[PDB]
Image (tube, coloured by chain):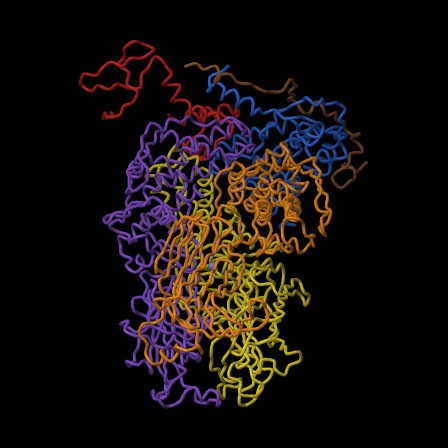
Chain colours: A red, B purple, C brown, D blue, E orange, F yellow
């Protein structure tokens, strides 16, 4: 993620700056000084909501899985309400993770 | 240990701060910490107990996070938090007891219970929060290999001893010279006695010494030194050195002459005080040497002179004493003092659950034996159990 | 799984209000006659008349 | 009926609204204090604010990036923009002295056996430039001809009334050196 | 009470953390709390005093909020904050004094001052903040009917009692057997004496027992036990049991024999120590039973044999003593200890404002009587006044 | 002083809170404070030491700001912070020692060391954080001239003095009468003795008085009052008033009669207790007046009538006594006490670095002499050095 894009958007929305002209060292100084400021309370609280609930949102998603255990051995298909038989693993316990 | 302290600290902060009507800005950081703890603990299984009468307990964590969107907390939020807090507090309590009741002769500083061994893992490092209590900060400093220090009010540094030494003695115990002492907790009372009142001594002065070595170095100690041993100033019937018979001690108290108190580190005089009583400071020492003289009064009124004849019949025995109290001190190693309750907590847990005597500590956590034979393994185990006791006391009262 | 009791909430707000932006259209400002306009020292700015 | 996450978002929105009650007291305090105390401006609260009137107060926290420290290009742009705005808002002078009459008297007094650039347009331009440059803290350089001792005479008043740190140091020393070495030390 | 504690806590945080130059990120949340306090208290009138000589004072709250648009707060911010802090601190002071100077036989836990009754309203609940102090923690716990614990350095648990029992006596008071004791604060000091030195007792052993029942159950207490009672080891002239005459006590001290100190809980022996001295732990107890014996020395040197004749005249009286000090302890109820100053603050306020004696507390807050008869109503009122006194001390010295 | 305290507080919080794995939200405010401190301290040069054996040290500050772009702290972040923390901690230690070892006759409250004078500038005000500690709070209150207060456990307010007064006496020292006291630390033990046992006194009563004026006003003090002087109740040989001979004192202890303890302020009785022993409260006083009496028993058994004859050969000397311990008190001025260690720290630094005797404090920081002559300059310098010692103790143990 290039914070130079964020700094360019910042300068652009300030509306008095021709962003194409700002020197490079000053752009990076601006990035460095922005990285040090504490976040505003409303924005930070919204971000906390999203960060605490993003795991659940991703798990709720239907077009992606969280991984695949291979296990190279005969494992009985689990029985679930959502589908008769599935290879659903509910946790990666007991397997090396890559 | 850091993880366990963080758990207890988080639970105590949740108890103190999550209250009805409080601004959520007051507990935003705390609730972030609480949710992080819940996330980290979720899906893990723990077992505690199994030694002595301590029941075997199984702990599973499947809790839901706490809300973060109210402006002021309400009763619903407080109850929802308290339900989880009770379970976490119970888990911390049992883990702390399991750690206290155990000991190891090798690597006593490392965790001994399986729950704490599991918490030692890297996955749980996300629960660290704060390390601001005295015992946890000393733990962290020691691990970082820096100077540590525990400040004690009346430290129990002297193993309980009460005994006498007779430099002059006879079977009849009619004419004795020597010293008697009580070293207990944080006080030393010493009394040199001579039955003849130094009638035949050179220059009519009898010298007395008393050396008290400590098991650990004490620093920046405030001490009270007073010129009389009130414990050895009344008639007594003591039993002989070998217990065969009993002898009489009818003291009459004189002022101690040429009082010198030396505080020594590595056998060298660090502090020294001459004829000075009251509050004194010993900056760094591991031995206390007290020297004091019984000087026969050169001038006596008749009532005084009649007490001390020049022949054997001696009904009054000239005694001179000192009393030394360590009010406060700082030590690198953990001790038992009059203000803290950590020794009491450890001993109480062990006695309540009837822990069999282990390979390290003395029976009943006898502090006299422990401080008499304060060894490296004993010190490590004692510090571990005291740190766990402080962690538990943060929550249990 | 959908749980009605855990999904049913009660949302509270205000009934109605108006949000203004100018904040100075409510201030009616006039200026004294320029000839007798005084400076910080309470004397006419231009006193050569 | 909302999912717990949806309810969290909506509850946060409901509990943390940015609107605040608005009253004539808030409006009056929003008026700048110096303007309020100035006796040249008469301000009245001739409007009634109902109890259910709200506003979103601006975030006027002083700059957190310190663009005046080691941001030469950005600070130059900022000062230029503020200068333009100040120029826009500075008032225009009225009923100046007659340009022809003043020029004639100046020519008679100077007896040039100089008078270029003197007019109402230039007077107004200088008034606006001075005030706006002071407002925006734009450095202003001085352009002059050393032979024009009348321009130097005017610059004497310029330096008297405008603080010396408003001019680039080279221009200030140039103007002062011209003044001394063509009027003062010579006199 | 929680709202009062929160007012004091936020005022203390404001007076500590609002100092010129400090970053605003250091006081953001504190200023939010302070502004909420101001908003809630604004437009309210309180009246304090009117009991005894405590002045009748009126409190009107109308304060502007503290600014929020500032990076590093400056002298203006500190001045505007301190002007409000002074008024709020004075208001809290007077509310606490009004609460302390009142008592109620019925509902001693309920607030007594009308100012605190007002603060009990649900409108003020928004100021609750964090209840992190020990006393407020215990207040909340006992409100919820949960376990409470107060840690004390030598708690004042024994009502003062200096007395003697004569198991054998006659008018001449020249052949007496019995015990003397002084219970005070945290020290029991007992001494059993026998004028005949157990000459005619079976096995030449005289038994002495001393039962001290506490009014409250102490837990995890460290206790220093010593084998002599220095208070009853010097000649005395004691007035008889009925004050008719006086009798002479000329003691000679022998070691106590078969010492047994046992700590009992509802009659069951929870802890017991046999002939052990130094530091010991009582995990949970409400009675102390000290049993000891005067054993006539089987063998005596002539200087001792002279002291104990067979016939009547007993010039010297054999005495065996014990000293017991509760150094530290934990109690469910509120007590007075050495370190804390809550009893002192409450008594000082009552004495200063000449509060008439009410129905609950004894005159002048006599701790001896208050702890001798520690009724439930007295405990409720004492906990209330001690909690409010700690709240007050959080701001005032 | 405030800036030095802020540096120490910031470093303590950095060491406690900046730990591996901790959530960044647990530290964000502290990190802002720490970066503010680094920015302020960068580019400045300091010099400490040069007095006594304290080594000269030069301190230069060029550090990078701690990051603010992590979710959970990792080993990298902790390692980067630790080096900065160590350097700052050493700097604070040396500044505190250099300030502690200095003193001034005039303006003793003002900073004395070059480093602290530099820190007193206006550029360093940006680091103030929070002045939570008791000593810094009282420092700020005293600077504002508000009312300060320090709470002490067993305050050292009585300079050590053991003495006696003889109201009746003769060359032979056979028929003495008078008082005999020890005042030390927080205890007063006073015994009034009469050899004739009030045989010829009016009403068979001998009156005794003892006045102990304190150097400072004590407030809300809890006192323990007991009816005997254990220290003065055994046979003694005591040097005469002029030291030219010795006399004999053979006490027999009676109950003190009409005991009256007065705590007085400006000569006005503030608290008065009659015949009440145990825990008492003195709300505000600067003098303690103990009055008691020896009343000849109207009725005596033969064993007492023998002790107390009419003629001169008095073998037993009647004695009454009183003991008074200040358990806990509050003082506007700073004092040494049992619990704390500030006097010990200051004395330790001075002794370790062999600081020459200066113009304010007595040699070796002798507390007896200091409290005996506790001048305003000594109070100022002592408060300064104690506050610096507290700041230092926040980091060094
Ligand atoms: Zn103590």
Q: Is residue B51 above or below residue D4?
A: below
Residue B382: % across, % down: 32, 51
Q: How many marks?
A: 0
Residue A61: % across, % down: 37, 15
Q: Residue at x 77, y 35 (%)?
A: D39
Q: Is residue E117 left or right of residue B238?
A: right
Q: Is residue F314 above or below residue E224?
A: below
Name of the residue lying farthest toward the right? C49
Q: Is residue E132 above or below residue D100?
A: below
Between F217 and E298, the one nearer to me in the picture: E298
Residue B235 visible here: yes
Between A89 and E244, the one nearer to me in the picture: E244
Q: In which quarter of the view is residue B332 placed?
A: bottom left
Name of the residue lying farthest toward the top? A84
Q: Is residue E78 above or below residue B157?
A: above
Q: Is residue B275 left or right of residue E126?
A: left
Residue D177 visible here: no
Q: Residue at x 29, y 80 (%)?
A: B169
Residue B195: % across, % down: 37, 82
Between F250 and F199, the one nearer to me in the picture: F199
Between E323 and B280, the one nearer to me in the picture: E323
Name of the residue lying farthest toward the left? A73
Residue B100: % across, % down: 33, 45
């Amino acid at each position: 993620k290039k914070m130079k894009a964020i700094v360019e958007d910042f300068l652009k929305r300030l509306h008095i700056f021709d962003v194409a002209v700002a020197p490079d060292d000053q752009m990076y100084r601006l990035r460095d000084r922005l990285r040090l400021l504490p976040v505003e309370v409303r924005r930070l609280d919204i971000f906390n909501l999203i960060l605490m609930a993003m795991d659940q949102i991703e798990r709720a998603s239907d077009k992606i899985a969280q991984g695949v255990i291979i296990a190279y051995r005969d494992m009985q298909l689990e029985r679930d309400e959502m589908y008769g038989y599935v290879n659903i693993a509910r946790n990666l316990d007991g397997f090396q993770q890559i | 240990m850091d993880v366990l302290y963080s758990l207890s600290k988080t639970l105590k902060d949740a108890r103190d701060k999550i209250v009805e009507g409080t601004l959520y800005s007051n507990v935003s950081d705390l609730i972030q910490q609480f949710n992080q703890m819940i996330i980290t603990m979720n899906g893990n299984e723990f077992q505690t107990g199994g030694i002595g009468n301590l029941p075997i307990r199984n702990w599973n964590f499947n809790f839901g996070l706490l809300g973060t969107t109210l402006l002021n907390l309400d009763a619903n939020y407080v109850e929802t938090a308290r339900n989880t807090i009770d379970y976490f507090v119970d888990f911390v309590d049992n883990v702390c007891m399991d750690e206290m009741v155990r000991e190891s002769q090798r690597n006593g500083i490392a965790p001994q219970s399986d729950s704490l061994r599991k918490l030692s893992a890297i996955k749980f490092k996300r629960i660290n929060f704060d390390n601001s209590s005295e015992y946890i900060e000393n733990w962290n400093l020691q691990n970082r290999r820096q100077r540590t220090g525990f400040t004690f009010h009346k430290p129990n540094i002297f193993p309980y001893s009460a005994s006498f030494t007779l430099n002059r003695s006879q079977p009849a115990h009619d004419n004795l010279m020597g010293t008697m002492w009580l070293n207990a907790g944080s006080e030393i009372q010493v009394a040199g006695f001579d039955y003849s009142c130094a009638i035949n001594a050179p220059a009519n002065i009898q010298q007395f010494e008393h050396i008290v070595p400590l098991r650990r170095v004490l620093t920046t100690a405030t001490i009270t030194l007073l010129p009389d041993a009130e414990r050895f100033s009344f008639p007594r019937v003591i039993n002989s050195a070998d217990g065969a018979t009993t002898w009489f001690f009818n003291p009459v108290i004189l002022r101690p002459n040429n009082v010198e108190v030396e505080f020594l580190l590595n056998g060298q005089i660090i502090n020294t005080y001459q004829a000075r009583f009251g509050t004194i400071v010993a900056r760094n020492f591991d031995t206390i040497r007290l020297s004091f003289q019984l000087m026969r009064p050169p001038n006596m009124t008749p009532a005084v002179a009649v007490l001390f004849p020049n022949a054997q019949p001696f009904e009054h025995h000239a005694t001179v004493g000192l009393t030394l109290r360590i009010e406060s001190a700082v030590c690198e190693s953990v001790l038992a003092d009059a203000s803290e309750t950590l020794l009491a907590n450890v001993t109480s847990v062990r006695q309540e659950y009837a822990i069999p005597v282990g390979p390290v500590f003395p029976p009943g956590m006898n502090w006299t034996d422990l401080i008499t034979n304060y060894s490296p393994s004993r010190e490590d185990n004692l510090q571990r159990v005291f740190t766990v006791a402080s962690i538990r006391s943060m929550l249990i009262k | 799984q959908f749980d009605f009791r855990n999904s049913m909430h009660m949302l509270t707000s205000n009934l109605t209000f108006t949000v203004y932006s100018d904040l100075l259209a409510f201030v009616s400002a006039d200026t004294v006659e320029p000839i007798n306009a005084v400076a910080f020292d309470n004397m006419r700015i231009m006193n050569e008349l | 009926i909302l999912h717990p996450i949806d309810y969290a978002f909506n509850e946060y929105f409901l509990q943390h609204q940015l609107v605040e009650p608005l009253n004539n007291d808030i409006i009056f305090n929003y008026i700048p204090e110096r303007i309020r105390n100035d006796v040249n401006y008469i301000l009245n609260m001739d409007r009634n604010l109902p109890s259910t009137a709200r506003y979103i107060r601006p975030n006027l926290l002083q700059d957190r990036l310190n663009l005046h420290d080691n941001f030469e290009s950005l600070w130059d742009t900022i000062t230029t923009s503020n200068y333009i705005l100040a120029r826009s808002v500075v008032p225009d002078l009225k009923e100046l002295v007659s340009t022809e009459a003043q020029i004639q008297k100046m020519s008679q007094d100077l007896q040039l056996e100089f008078l270029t650039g003197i007019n109402s347009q230039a007077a107004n331009d200088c008034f606006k430039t001075l005030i706006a440059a002071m407002l925006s803290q734009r450095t202003m350089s001085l352009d002059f001809v050393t032979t024009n001792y009348m321009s130097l005479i005017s610059g004497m008043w310029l330096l008297t009334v405008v603080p010396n740190d408003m001019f680039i140091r080279e221009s200030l020393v140039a103007c002062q050196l011209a003044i001394v070495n063509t009027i003062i030390y010579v006199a």
